[PDB]
Image (cartoon, rainbow over all chains, first blue to last red; front, side, top):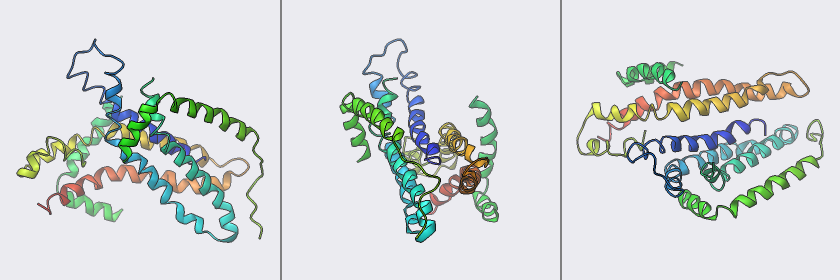
Length: 139
Length: 44
Length: 96
């Protein structure tokens, strides 16, 4: 449950985020001082349109790409067995919560200077991209 | 299938809310009364 | 990087070729990720970090089962920002 904590929250935010920029376009395409409880209802439940499947299945990946560990026999299995169990239940919790409670609780309730350092090297990667699949292979 | 499942829950909201509330109070009782030990039993 | 080549800048590509238009659909699937991304790698490493400090009863085993994750979560993100894109721009050109 200690290692799970870093993913239960990663489940929520990636949904909250695509909803922060979804509520930054219906604000640039429409007025600004006119919005109802249904006008706010539609915008957040339209961020769950895209990322929806993306995460519940990616935390379905986190929970299943771990199953093989249960095949640990004897002493070591009795040890990390219980760890795998709790890590999994706690994920199935946050995952099956980000589809019943998370979208709702977020509806009932300096990024510049990292974007500046990334994309100079991003476009640089688009130079001969086949050369960066070569440096990677060297890593 | 996930999207439809998001929509149905959003519809439920406020019956769902109280379920996650009663779970939170129930998930607080069990924890308090949970046995304890250094490690899981590993002996054969 | 898929729904970026499935929006309206993805009406230009399927019909005809335009590298400086799929590079614009890639530059946005790049500044739209930097926000959800940098925080995913944040909450993952930040919440995974405390256990890496192995002092106390039982710490030993946890710091060992965490270091690989914490370490693997530095090169997994950092590197993937350059491998996945510059390889989807290379695979979108084969079927084309």
